[PDB]
Amino acid sequence: INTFDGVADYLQTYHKLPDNYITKSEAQALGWVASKGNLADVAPGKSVGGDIFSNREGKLPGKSGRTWREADINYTSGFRNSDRILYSSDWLIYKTTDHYQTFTKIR
Image 1 (cartoon, rainbow, N blue to C red):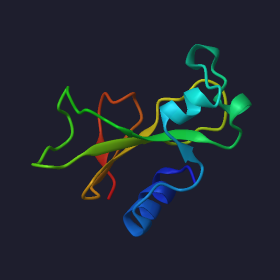
Image 2: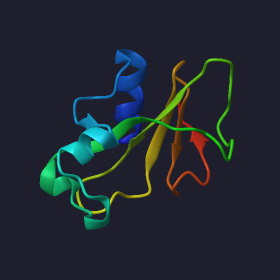
Image 3: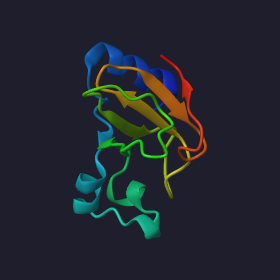
Image 4: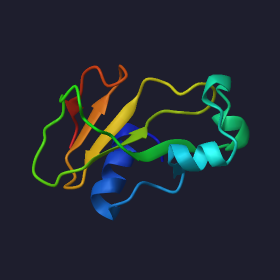
């Protein structure tokens, strides 16, 4: 599952990202080399997702004790694309299609 709707629904319902996601640290460990654009070479079918998103430009809504995490969307192979899903600890879901420049709420 790696589509906006698909990951959005999965998260709200199962409260974890689907099995095709790995964090950046786990992908680095597995052999992911960002400037080589090789994720799909060292980890076919996998997307990076689950890392904490700091929210410093402060574009997404904050709240006492709320954490934001991210996951890449639409990724198949090559260099990571510009699409990301943003999900809080309390399950508000937002998406970005321009490298966190703008966000739209989707759930």
